[PDB]
Length: 57
Length: 42
Ligand SMILES: [Zn+2]
Image (cartoon, rainbow over all chains, first blue to last red; front, side, top):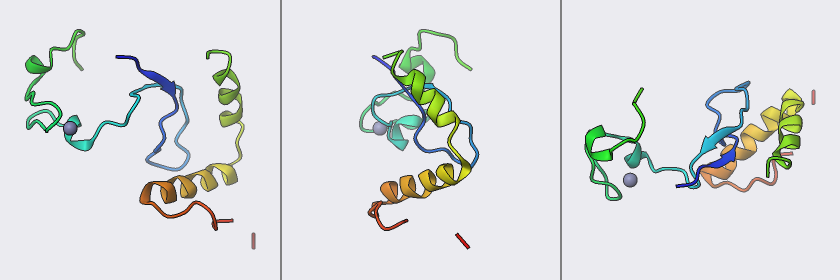
């Protein structure tokens, strides 16, 4: 999918440097960020199920 | 669009701290749901 080009809206602290970043078109829900337990949107539970094209970090 | 955000970089980099702080509270009021108006020195 396309990644929109823009600054991150919520900077966690004051003075955080604004940087042009790759961004999802819609902010992912907090349940979609977690890996071990899936959510209603995606039922994957590990990086094998997600099937990332690139190597992880 | 690469020619459009080239000035967004130049504007967001030169904003004063008073503008950065003002942009922080207003954004939070937007997130918590309070009206952004009414926010607007010793
Ligand atoms: Zn989810």
